[PDB]
């Protein structure tokens, strides 16, 4: 509940990358 | 009736496969490291790999 | 509109035509390496439905609870079983079954004859962590991930299991239990 | 304002042949760029994030013209009429690429897509200037 403002961008990118998906 | 008719390829035990293909694996690493992927040798290796994958579908 | 086939298959009879290989290259070495791998995969699983689901936030043992129920069953039966199981993993298995069937139809297979012929899991990349314990000791805190692969084939050997089906509760104007005549039960 | 509105009114209903002429006009007004080197050495972290935007704009407009010249008249009318439904027709796109014998289905689809994007952009602007 106290996440840093200077790393908001990097948390967003990790959330997008670490999602399930089908290969090709 | 002749060698060609009765010739068969033996099946390599799973535990011995890292020794039967050691030379071929080294060569592919040798070619890509020194000549690059935009090379005539690299293209030949890729074509042979396509043949092996295609035969898996039986 | 299938991807090109660049070599003969291993089937007894050939069903497609081999096409000449491309003569152009990709601009970068990284792009060229990635595309060669994609071409290799396109030579496989022809005349069958396949799916490959990556980075499921579950473990091998949790996924095997559901997968062991659907092996060697007809597609219709397997799909129904995955719906009724109240497990978080059952949701991912259901998505894979639908994705694979859509793949089979694009290849020109009849969905009414599909059978689940192969299913297995594969290890993903793990998120490592640590949790403290008593008296200064420490332990592991790991989040696991797994890959799921499903293959559907036509007229493959299948199990005879079949489930009975009943209708749900009738609610609305379609329910007519209030028209029952209870005067008959007073007679002999 | 009014001249802009008239141009946008015509552009939103423009066909593929019109798009080819459009591309030719944009190229006619363009000075052809030389390729530019990245600002840093190969070991630098930004080496691979460099994009030669000027070269790409030129190359892509040239590609649009070349693909539209393999596309037949019946196909062009089908494209103008279907919009998104042409872009999602893989058999159509594959046929064009096979006829070409060089460009691939992805390139063909992007060229057709930009034609439609041009028309859609003109409609959005038309509302802006007209209102
Ligand atoms: Mg302490």
Image (cartoon, coloured by chain):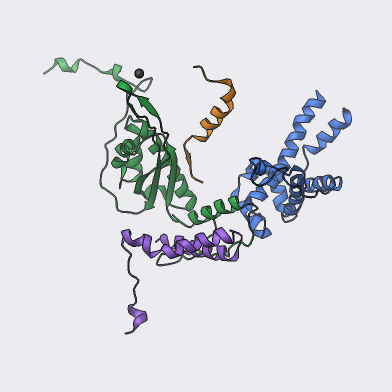
Chain colours: A orange, B purple, C green, D blue
Residue with the most extreme left position: C188
User: Depth check: B34 or C86 in front?
Assistant: B34
Write down the quadrant of residue A12 in the picture: top right
Above or below: residue C182 compared with residue C83: above
Q: Residue furthest bottom?
A: B1
D9 w.r.t. C103: above or below = above
Whole-percent x and y of residue C25?
A: 63, 57
Q: Tell whether A8 sits left or right of C67.
A: right
The residue depicted at 74 percent of the width and 47 percent of the height is D37
x, y percent for residue D12:
77, 37
Give residue C178's quadrant in the image: top left
The foreground one among D114 and C163 is D114
**Rendered-image quadrant of the N terminus of chain C:** bottom right
Residue closer to the observer: C77 or C34 = C34
Residue D96 image point, x, y percent: 66, 55
The structure residue drawn at horizontal position 29% and vertical position 35%, both measured from the top left corner, is C165
Q: How many marks?
A: 0
Relative horizontal placement of residue C142, taking residue C27 as reference (left or right): left
Q: Position of residue D86 (x, y in %)?
A: 65, 45
Q: Is residue C10 left or right of residue D52?
A: left
Name the quadrant of the C terminus of chain C: top left
Q: Determine the residue positioned at 32% across, 25% down.
A: C137
Q: Is D85 above or below relative to C43?
A: above
Describe residue C185's horizontal placement relative to residue D34 as left or right. left
Q: Residue at x 44, y 45 (%)?
A: C52
Front position in the image: C152 or B53: B53
Ligand 1, by image quadrant, is top left
């Amino acid at each position: 509940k106290f996440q840093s403002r200077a790393e908001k961008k990097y948390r967003i990118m990790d959330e997008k990358v670490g999602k399930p998906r089908f290969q090709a | 009736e002749g060698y060609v008719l009765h010739e068969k390829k033996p099946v390599v035990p799973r535990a011995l496969r890292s020794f039967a293909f050691k030379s071929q694996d080294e060569h592919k690493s040798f070619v890509l490291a020194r000549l690059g992927i935009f090379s005539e040798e690299a293209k030949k290796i890729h074509l042979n790999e396509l043949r092996t994958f295609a035969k898996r579908d039986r | 509109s299938r991807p090109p086939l660049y070599a003969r298959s291993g089937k007894f009879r050939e069903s497609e035509e081999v096409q000449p290989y491309r003569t152009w290259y990709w601009y970068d070495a990284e792009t060229e390496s990635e595309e060669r791998r994609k071409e290799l995969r396109q030579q496989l699983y022809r005349d069958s439905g396949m799916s490959y689901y990556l980075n499921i936030p579950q473990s091998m043992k949790k996924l095997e609870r559901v997968v062991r129920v659907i092996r060697n069953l007809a597609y219709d039966e397997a799909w129904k079983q995955a719906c009724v199981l109240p497990l978080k993993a059952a949701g991912f298995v259901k998505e894979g079954l639908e994705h694979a069937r859509k793949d089979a139809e694009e290849k020109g297979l009849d969905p009414k004859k599909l059978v689940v012929s192969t299913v297995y899991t594969a290890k993903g990349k793990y998120l490592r962590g640590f949790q403290p314990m008593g008296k200064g000791f420490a332990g592991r805190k790991t989040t696991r991930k797994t890959h799921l692969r499903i293959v559907l084939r036509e007229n493959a050997s299948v199990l005879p299991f079949a489930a009975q089906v009943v209708s749900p509760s009738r609610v609305g104007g379609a329910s007519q239990k209030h028209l029952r005549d209870i005067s008959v039960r007073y007679t002999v | 304002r009014d001249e802009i509105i008239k141009l946008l009114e015509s552009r939103k209903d423009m066909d593929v042949n019109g798009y080819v002429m459009y591309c030719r006009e944009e190229l006619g007004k363009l000075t052809v760029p030389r390729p530019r080197a990245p600002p840093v050495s190969p070991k630098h972290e930004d080496y691979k994030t460099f994009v030669d935007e000027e070269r790409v704009t030129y190359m892509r407009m040239k590609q649009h013209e070349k693909i539209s010249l393999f596309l037949t008249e019946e196909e062009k009318n089908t494209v103008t009429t279907k919009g998104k439904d042409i872009l999602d027709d893989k058999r159509f796109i594959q046929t064009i690429a096979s006829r070409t014998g060089f460009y691939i289905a992805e390139e063909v689809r992007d060229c057709l897509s930009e034609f439609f994007n041009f028309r859609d952009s003109s409609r959005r602007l038309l509302t802006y200037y007209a209102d």
